[PDB]
Image (cartoon, coloured by chain):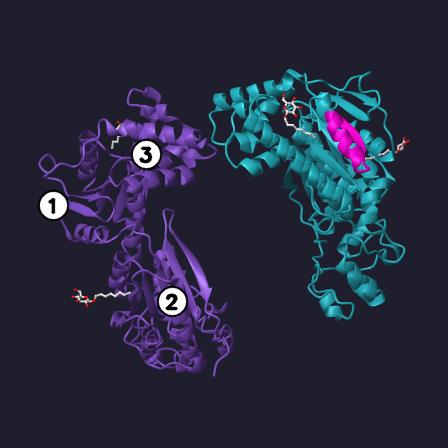
Chain colours: A purple, B cyan
């Protein structure tokens, strides 16, 4: 049975923000999911600016439009989950009344879905006030609109929902599966989690937050096998890799960060880069570089020589196909789920890891497709500072002024199983 | 002495449209010119939506902003004409009062410029009403605004200018050089044209219009020297070039065009393509293909052999450098000025010409830079239908279902005077 997630909440209460994070997380871990924003449907259908009057409960024209947009969205939810192979559909709309919630629930019931409600409730002044500014500066609804006039207007639109608003009740809704989030990341009320997927959605939802912070991602400094153009293994740092560690410590200091937590893997290269900082670090094997199996410590030249078929097939689909006894990037994403979860929970954090591990992490926060993920650029001696925002997540690349080898291998043009070694190794950086 | 063109007129009276055409025409014929839209300066400075109230004569805040934007624009006019080498500056603003007009005139006088006024006055209902719709659908000022509210608002903004509006007078302004355009292309009043440049600006301005029509551009059908990969000459049509003429006649018919005027050059290939139509045509030598001088009828191979230096230098700057005894595209643009002027004056017109001639014409209507002009794509057996619009000019390419050779030669990567013949002729299409 597919799952219908029904958002619930007043306008500008983080309902859409949560809808996006949840869709992204579920897709990242391989659960085909799509969100359906009723407001966007309205925008696409009307194509003209609408004042708060359009949202009044007695406004017969705006009432019909919002009602047909909502039905259009639900038809699409049905198409996705019953025809397109979707597993989870996120219905993003205010859904503030019991009547409405019971209709959607019956929609799910008629289509053989399990329904689960996610209500977002803000009460924190700063959160609420900032959300309106975020809505006023980023919503397509309020473009080229006077500041005060837009604010006042949206303010009146929220009122249109507030008067008949009924939060999920402890008794009235005791037979419904749901989670109520009070001020994103602060408090929660959970009721009747029906299955494994709802259990994981709850676990994820109960661990995200909006506390201002930055995620610092960087690979260990240049290693020994790095200079040799060799992949995997357990090398130590190289002269330049040591030179980096010292630039990293200074960087971390100049940054003057509030309670920075540092993580590394069980590999000497990360650990020794961490050992150069002032602050303590924690090491985990879940953060270890992707396993190259039989191709561990080889150069690409050597891979082309002993495993030309696997090498060409990996180039064809670098996300799914693996070396014998190795891991695929798809395997790595799954291994990295507890890391994803903890990075969400953390505040200011620095992760000294590896190239493949770092690509998976960058793909998560920057929302890159599974196809592009294995090809993301994670240069040595560079710190990728990620700062989660309302729209998504900004990224700043900070080169820490130390020379290093290039380990980035572009996908070669010829990926034929019957290709010449010169064409298979054409996109390799200098090595030895 | 540089020239300051001062636009004058009510909002939505074609003032900006004329400002653009005039700047484009002057630049095309090689007179460095730039326009200065005071409304755009205001947009860039305020960066927030402004109602009609912002434009009220008693509104002390909007009065200061419009006044500093106007002075900023004039400072830039000064920088362009006195520091950047500009020849003509077009000051686009309502400039509806004598006081204002006299200030701008004194600005010109203090900076050693000759001032010339261009007033646009619409009275034709359909023109005026359509302009407001064009303004409402294309002005950045009215984005995401309610239709009726935007119209009403702009309507009130025009009122802000109408009450103190004083058109250029026959007696009051007898000492000023100017031209008053009443309903774009209908009537004109001209006073004291001071020099040659004002004389040409008047001549151009008195010949443009907004009567709905299309300009059909197409080269003669595939010729004999075309198949041989030979440039210039006076060949006749080839079997496919004849096959085209017949597709052209049918096209022109299926189009069912209102009083279509057809033009051709004094060359057999255009004339014979025209001879296949039902309608009469007129031939002019001003429409003759660019002169290749000593390289007439040669192939590129042959050019590389006898004139490798001129061939490499032409590839370096195809707009300005010419073959010995030949014309440059820059020479051709000038030769084509009477053609430009007449195409402006015409209504529905079809020009059966040549590749280089067609590039110059396409560059005019589509506003392409002099650098890009010699490289515009003008394929054989294809009709380029240009339709002048408010924003600029839309273009539709219509392939008339007849195979033909490719005569388009891209600029080769190596344009060194000391390059190998293989690298000079690398971008040549198949020929013989
Ligand atoms: C699945 C059925 C969806 C029906 C969508 C109805 C659209 C009408 O919009 C209504 O606006 C009211 C504002 O007070 C809210 O309280 C209602 O919950 C909302 O549905
Ligand atoms: C990027 C850094 C993220 C590191 C993720 C560490 C995940 C915790 O790893 C382990 O998970 C077990 C699961 O119950 C716990 O019982 C252990 O106490 C914990 O150490
Ligand atoms: C070169 C001097 C430019 C001065 C710009 C002043 C900007 C004030 O805007 C004024 O709005 C009025 C609306 O009734 C018009 O009549 C004035 O002509 C216009 O200047
Ligand atoms: C694209 C077709 C445009 C053709 C432009 C024809 C230009 C007119 O060409 C000639 O110009 C002379 C200039 O005074 C006139 O005296 C002649 O009568 C006219 O034939």
Q: Nearer the viewer, mark 2 or mark 1?
A: 2
Question: What span is colored magenta in the figure?
Answer: B101-118
Asked if ligand 1 lies within 8 A of label 1, the reply is: no
Looking at the image, which residue is at 70% across and 49% down? B376
The secondary element bearing badge 1 is classed as loop
To which chain does the residue with label 2 belong?
A
Q: Nearer the viewer, residue A105 or A258?
A: A258
Q: Residues within 10 Å of mark 3 (few under 14, many from 20)?
A: some
First in sequence: mark 2 or mark 3?
A: 3
Res B247 seen here: no
Q: Nearer the viewer, residue B377 or B2?
A: B2
Q: Are marks 2 and 3 on the same chain?
A: yes
First in sequence: mark 1 or mark 3?
A: 3
Q: Residues within 10 Å of mark 2 (few under 14, many from 20)?
A: few
Looking at the image, which residue is at 71% across and 18% down? B166
The x and y percentages for residue B85 are 78, 46
- Residue A92, located in which quarter of the rendered image? top left
Magenta stretch: residue B117 in it?
A: yes
The Cα atoms of the two marked residues, 2 and 3, are separated by 53 Å
Residue, disc 2 = A253
- Residue A160, located in which quarter of the rendered image? top left
The secondary element bearing badge 2 is classed as helix
Q: Nearer the viewer, mark 1 or mark 3?
A: 1
Residue, disc 1 = A192
Q: Residues within 10 Å of mark 1 (few under 14, many from 20)?
A: some
**Residue B384 sits above or below residue B428 on the image:** above
Q: Nearer the viewer, mark 2 or mark 3?
A: 2
Residue, disc 3 = A72
């Amino acid at each position: 049975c597919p799952t219908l997630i029904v958002m619930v909440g007043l306008p500008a209460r983080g309902k859409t923000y949560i809808s996006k994070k949840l869709t992204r997380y579920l897709n990242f871990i391989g659960v085909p999911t799509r969100e359906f924003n009723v407001g966007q449907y309205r925008r696409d259908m009307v194509k003209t600016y609408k004042s708060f009057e359009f949202f009044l409960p007695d406004n017969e024209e705006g009432l019909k439009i919002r009602k047909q947009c909502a039905l259009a969205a639900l038809n699409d939810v049905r198409k996705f989950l019953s025809e397109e192979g979707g597993h989870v559909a996120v219905f993003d709309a205010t859904n503030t009344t019991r009547e409405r919630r019971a209709m959607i629930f019956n929609f799910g019931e008629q289509n053989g879905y399990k329904t689960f409600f996610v209500e977002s409730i803000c009460v924190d002044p700063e959160v609420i006030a900032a959300n309106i500014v975020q809505v006023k500066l980023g919503s397509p609804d309020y473009v080229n609109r006077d500041s005060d006039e837009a604010t006042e207007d949206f303010m009146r639109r929220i009122e249109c929902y507030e008067n008949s608003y009924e939060s999920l009740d402890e008794e009235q809704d005791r037979d419904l599966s749901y989670i109520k989030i009070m001020d994103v990341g602060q408090s929660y009320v959970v009721n009747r989690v029906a299955d494994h997927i709802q259990s994981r959605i709850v676990y994820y939802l109960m661990n995200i937050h909006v506390t201002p912070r930055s995620i610092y991602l960087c690979r260990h400094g240049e290693s020994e096998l790095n200079l040799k153009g060799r992949i995997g293994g357990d090398p130590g740092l190289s002269p330049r890799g040591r030179e980096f560690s010292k630039h990293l410590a200074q960087f971390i200091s100049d940054q003057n960060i509030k309670d920075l937590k540092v993580f590394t893997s069980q590999m000497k290269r990360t650990i020794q880069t961490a050992e150069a900082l002032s602050v303590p670090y924690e090491q985990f094997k879940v953060l270890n570089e992707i396993d190259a199996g039989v191709c561990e410590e080889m150069t690409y030249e050597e891979i082309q020589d002993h495993y030309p078929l696997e090498f060409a097939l990996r180039d064809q689909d670098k996300y799914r196909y693996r070396y014998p006894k190795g891991e695929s990037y798809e395997d790595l994403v799954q291994r990295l789920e507890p890391v994803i979860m903890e990075l969400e929970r953390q505040e200011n954090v620095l992760v000294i890891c590896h190239q493949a591990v770092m690509r998976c992490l960058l793909a998560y926060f920057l929302d890159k497709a599974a196809e592009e993920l294995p090809y993301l650029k994670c240069p040595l001696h560079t710190v990728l500072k990620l700062t989660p925002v309302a729209y998504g997540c900004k990224v700043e690349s900070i080169f820490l002024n130390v020379a290093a080898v290039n380990t980035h291998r572009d996908r070669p043009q010829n990926v034929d199983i019957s290709r010449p070694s010169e064409e298979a190794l054409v996109t390799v950086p200098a090595h030895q």
